Length: 383
Image (cartoon, rainbow, N blue to C red; front, side, top):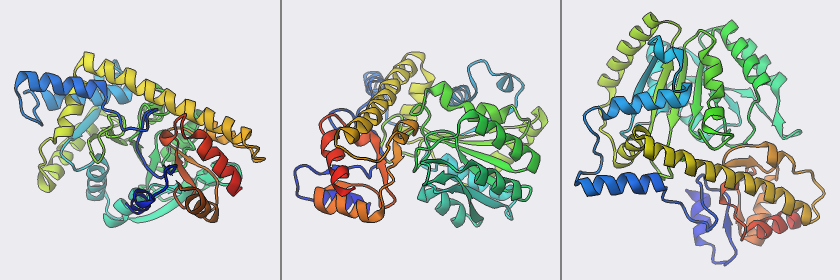
């Protein structure tokens, strides 16, 4: 809210907001996705109210989410080992998961990445867990401190909840590769830790299918895996919390038990009907034609971000900056840690009207061909 307020108030014509957390197109606008336009045109032509879903609409959405996570013909889905609770009513899946995990073991510690989105820490701390951080981002290499990460996990007590970004790390853009995911899974299993995967940016990293790899690797490790899906970013629905909580369990018997406890926890805590936005996502993911349209456009969006990462590195070079910025191309999703100091971020803002987070976080999705040079040349001046 605050960086944004200051940017909105800045009277200079060449100002750029890299502090945001949403996708914009080449024109610098928040897109109305074709699938969303088309789901809405269909609802209006049918004469139905906002928020509408057909009789089997919630079930069809839950099924569609499980398929996005695990693949259209997964055996886990077959064995009855996946439970999903919709989060279409403005209570996000992360909150539903935190509340559910707190019923199972309120004394658990929660481990989050160093650094992590403000809301990971706030959510779990507010919920009553002791929150600790595992080593993750390494400012010296612009990569992962993986030795530090595994040593931390290897020291945690059984039942410790480990919150992992499946892909598109917020705020750093630094993701694990598979050698790393495999080793994390092995430690989580050996130490009896509880993995809670946040997948809010599925489709913004490598592909919808590739971005779920961490979920598929955990699901194959014969343990209970908690997954918070969120779709507001991929659907360009600013402020929505639309998503779903999925739990992959180690047996059909464990799924029956988890589902009965989950139902009781949700009935006790909240009954939130689908929002306008939540019903749009449900309608789109339920329809093969609309879904295909979303998949295609999300690809275009993912590819524009990749073009901006490539472009920024090239323009930083062209501006004569001596530092190696190749890490920007290795980072994934909407964000990068630029590596600028807080003083350098102050200068960018004050002298050039380029707004980044004090941590150096920039939103690469806010770049376009009309601001690349403005941004690159300003960074060069500050460095």
